[PDB]
Image (cartoon, coloured by chain):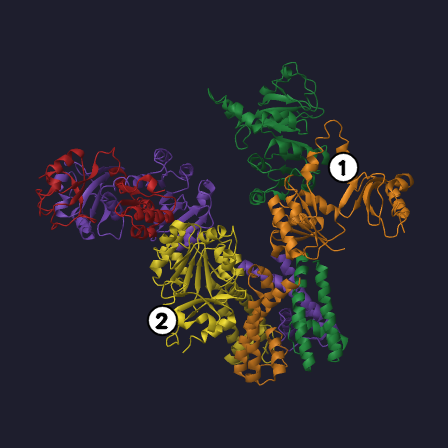
Chain colours: A yellow, B purple, C red, D green, E orange
Amino acid sequence: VPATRILLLVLAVIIYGTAGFHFIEGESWTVSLYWTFVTIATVGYGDYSPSTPLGMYFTVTLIVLGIGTFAVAVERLLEFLISRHVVICGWSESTLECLRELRGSEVFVLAEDENVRKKVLRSGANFVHGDPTRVSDLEKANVRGARAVIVDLESDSETIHCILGIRKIDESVRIIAEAERYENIEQLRMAGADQVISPFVISGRLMSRSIDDGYEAMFVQDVLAEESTRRMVEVPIPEGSKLEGVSVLDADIHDVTGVIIIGVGRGDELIIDPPRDYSFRAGDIILGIGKPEEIERLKNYISA
Amino acid sequence: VPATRILLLVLAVIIYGTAGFHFIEGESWTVSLYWTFVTIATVGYGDYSPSTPLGMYFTVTLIVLGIGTFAVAVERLLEFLISRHVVICGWSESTLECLRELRGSEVFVLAEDENVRKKVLRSGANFVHGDPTRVSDLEKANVRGARAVIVDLESDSETIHCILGIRKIDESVRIIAEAERYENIEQLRMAGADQVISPFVISGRLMSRSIDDGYEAMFVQDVLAEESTRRMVEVPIPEGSKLEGVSVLDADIHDVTGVIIIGVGRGDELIIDPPRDYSFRAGDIILGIGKPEEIERLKNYISA
Amino acid sequence: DLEKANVRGARAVIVDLESDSETIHCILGIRKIDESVRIIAEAERYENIEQLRMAGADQVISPFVISGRLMSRSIDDGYEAMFVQDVLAEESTRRMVEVPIPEGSKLEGVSVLDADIHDVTGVIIIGVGRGDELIIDPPRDYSFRAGDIILGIGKPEEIERLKNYISA
Amino acid sequence: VPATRILLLVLAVIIYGTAGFHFIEGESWTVSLYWTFVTIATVGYGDYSPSTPLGMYFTVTLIVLGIGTFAVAVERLLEFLISRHVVICGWSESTLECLRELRGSEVFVLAEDENVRKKVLRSGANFVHGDPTRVSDLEKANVRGARAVIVDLESDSETIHCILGIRKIDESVRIIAEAERYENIEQLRMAGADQVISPFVISGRLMSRSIDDGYEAMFVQDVLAEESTRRMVEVPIPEGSKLEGVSVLDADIHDVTGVIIIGVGRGDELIIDPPRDYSFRAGDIILGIGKPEEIERLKNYISA
Amino acid sequence: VIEIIRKHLPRVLKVPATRILLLVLAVIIYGTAGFHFIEGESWTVSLYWTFVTIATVGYGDYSPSTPLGMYFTVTLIVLGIGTFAVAVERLLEFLISRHVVICGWSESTLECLRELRGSEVFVLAEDENVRKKVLRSGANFVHGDPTRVSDLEKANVRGARAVIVDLESDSETIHCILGIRKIDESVRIIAEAERYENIEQLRMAGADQVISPFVISGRLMSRSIDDGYEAMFVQDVLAEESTRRMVEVPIPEGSKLEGVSVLDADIHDVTGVIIIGVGRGDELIIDPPRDYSFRAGDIILGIGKPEEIERLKNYISA
């Protein structure tokens, strides 16, 4: 049945109700409409009632009509009722441990499988069912407003196809991709990806360096865990700092603060172990390791 | 449970209730009947309630009896109370692009998947769930009174088994099939399809002409597009025209109109580039390419 | 595994893989090896034609669009599918060919109206190709150029009468 | 959750409410019970109300408390208010065309798959989900009371296992089985099957006899179809007939009735084309072909 | 009647109780505040009245006094009761030695469940079709993957008496034994080996007793060629319906046989059981020698009638 049949039947009764109480009892529309509601509601507060054989007749008829149409309209109603965001294209084991560190923000997981709807909703993310290679299904997941898009699909052919689809929707958003083979690192980066993270090349080099002594693999998997003592943080150099123009040899950040200056980055490059003649500028980002008591001693050090 | 089984129980409660108010409470019939209904409807205005223990036990009993049977009766009453088309058998990418040019007509889609229901209803076509190779599930899609049936199934064995099921319903509808292999073009014409469209023979013979110059594959993919400047339309010659018996050299269509006469079809045969001594008749369908400013110039020249 | 198959010394690469994402990825691998080879791709979905052509493919043939357009045009009369599937077959009576306009030809600057190619020769001029565009049904004031390509439909005895009419 | 568990929960509430009004408001037992009931039944009449904040808290609690279980008890109460069989083991294409001629009787289809529940219920049969090789799942399907059990399983190893399982449940029931290979005809028959029907040996011999002329295969598939003109029927010879002691040559049934005596069967054997010296006895069953007007002329012929 | 509708539509019980609660609370707030600020009721009354109003009772001790009160109340009731009915339905939905845990469901654990009808048994399996077989046998079913530590803790592995692991392969049986030993290293794991070569891997992972059935079966099908008496003895003394049973009788502290040799004890002469082994700790000596000295703590493995078993316990008693 059309929803409009249900609605018209409801409306017909309140009109009937209101009008008859007026015609039979001589009551005003305010109380007539109200009383009709009171009877439909089956509450009976005790103010208005019919006081004539016809009013009683009318009222009983009215109640039957009222509840019937009301209850139907209500069940339909109930049935109907029943910074920026980050978009994650594809669901895998790399984007699952990425989602635990992105708690608190809005995350939209665009995935082809419907089976993965329970695991996405359990971890605190909105699921958007679609194919992440289709441009019409990326726009559904609100890619254009996002602050970053994380692409980790089944192959490296679908990862370039999803990267090329974002570069025409928004040519300014930050794309982070995951390469599976070493040949496609410069292929995903030319097609638009701002950061290419290859997990089988990191783990391929941490397994050939753990044969003699595995301290290279213990440094990498402990400075990234956000439950240890030291945390690899990065702080930016603001405008009008005390270090805008000093060399690294004269700044001497490790002794006066306690952090370790493993590298500094200007723009889109990184200089690991900067030499002593490196003049600090404004806008630089200092990548460092230290205890969180030493980080606040560095943040006040680089202030105005 | 007949409706009348339910209705008897409801009335029995009503009569019982009404009479007790009448002889236990001493109420007149208009108020006792009213009260009984109201009691059943549990409204409680505040006018009548039992004023003696007999009535109190009686009324509590009426209420529970009333609610059970009333609720059922109401639930049941409400549940009881409140040219031609084209049919597309199967869903693939070739029938998705066919559905884009059939938005003005009404289209049924007979496919056995359930996941494709969201793609069909978006495109503006009614979805009929069923197996297209079965005669019982072909009759649900209104094959018998259709304009044309378009068969595109997963293989060429099921396309033949679906063409022979349509020809069992009626031998007058127009079947337009699609061949997957080149060798099965002659089997799909013996089963009963009127037009067999083999896309991988058109595509494979355009990827071999596009090695030197890609002008053959640029002409085919452009005149079929309705957004193009020139269009390929079939102009029929009406009965009582000024061109019956006239040869192609004596007519000179390209000089006076401006369209390009690339073929003339009589019945179900087409003669591409017809010779000079080809005599026209009434009934021959002219296949031409021209601007839309030139097409109505052609119909006004061959008119009666 | 592309450099095994001699893509550098080739004259045309025809990319038709199992899905549309692998056809873009293989086109991107060919353009790293030889930047001037002629790639002839094949799109499955309609929306991926502008991506296959941006990634490097010169000609994109989409078979599910040519078949979808010829299905909905064959409901009333099927003379447009009987035209396409018959001029391409090389066992047919009439062939669709391309002839080039040589340098120093008889038709330098000559318009198509006063050339009268269908009257003189008998071939049907459906388009004049210049470079990387095709003009279907060129207008009457269209002037030629030494170096055009005439696309036409005609009998095989009428193509030799066309090449001898455009000869130098 | 027994219905009585629900009822106990309800009673606890009505008892509780009644006592609290008695001790909180100081009301009598008769009115406190009435009031609590009426309150739960949400009538709203306006006679009894709490007069203290404690009474208010109490009353509100009773309403929310009692209404839940009140409604549920009503649901349970309303739910309470409102020849022999043939068992078919396994679902296939042989037991589907067997089920169409067994319309009108009770048929229980014991099958392992749950997918086949829709096709069994559509054809007019009760579905019993179980494994037909398990003796505990045959007894669930009521094999012991049946008049015949039809076994058609996936292999001939499961068909002997289902036949052996019935022979210990009931050693008198009639088992009809279907053999797949020719070697197992005497193996299924020794394990207990009363009739072994091998479809690939009938169809293997009807395909090697249809090469020259296919009249052998047209006779078999037309005398079994119950929509043709002639029907292969069998009538029994009763006690005290007119033929108990006559030979076939002197009975001369084909001329005086019109049926064709293809064979007669005594006990558990069949004699096809009985000779002229064959003396008819009592209890014999005459297998014959004829029009249904000729069958009634034969049935009265063999009477008392 | 909405409760009728709810019974008609349990099909929409798809959302969190938390959404349900927030919405009903918003309604009672609307109601109570209007009674306090529009009708002029006290907060005790306003809430009381609001409840009564929402619940659709409407006694009339309090009633709207102005058109505004009437308009207000109509809204309050029409929205509140619907929500109320929903909240009620969700509540009803919600309202209505130690154990052993069995990881996995096969035919070997089906016959183990017949012997354990007196104890309470959890079954941790990842199939859903097996729920009808477990509840028939009298064991609580816990859905989950037994190789996961999070789904092992749902089955109460940490406070169990013994855990019985029988999974589909020997790789998952090892991956489940190592997940149980991560929860607690004191529970008793009883595993089952599918191949003979993986008996030593399942003891290194942490199982206390590895029961390889295809090595017992394969070594009984090779002794039953000549005479089938070896495979007739094993399949009979394990049955509790047999006339003889193999029971372990422990020697208590302060017994009359500490230091006594087997020849000086002569158990088979005085009792009538056959002493086929003596276990000390986790080692078993089948057919112990003559000069084997008893102690307190040695578990005697014997075969005898039930009329002879309590005769043995009364002979070794303190």
Circle 2 residues within 10 Å: few <14, some 14–19, many ≥20: some
Q: Mark 2: which amino acid?
A: Arg
| Residue A267 left/right relative to D129 | left
Label 1, secondary structure: give it.
helix
Taking the spot 25% from the left edge, 34% from the top edge, the residue there is C90
| Residue D219 left/right relative to E300 | left
Using the image as rendered, state which of residue B138 and residue E318 is in the foreground. Answer: E318
- Give residue C11's position: percent from left, percent from top: 26, 41
Name the disc covering residue C2, or none.
none
Using the image as rendered, state which of residue B106 and residue A278 is in the foreground. Answer: A278
Q: Image height check: is B76 above or below E218?
A: below
Using the image, name the chain to which the residue with label 2 belongs. A
Give the residue furthest to the right. Answer: E270
Give the residue furthest to the bottom. Answer: E40
Taking the spot 70% from the left edge, 23% from the top edge, the residue there is D282
Using the image as rendered, state which of residue B51 and residue D13 is in the foreground. Answer: D13
Mark whose residue sits in front, 1 or 2: 2
> In which quadrant is the C terminus of chain D drawn?
top right
Name the disc covering residue E234, or none.
1
Q: Which residue is mark 2?
A: A281
Q: Image height check: is D211 above or below D5?
A: above
The answer, for residue D48, to whether it is visible in the render is no
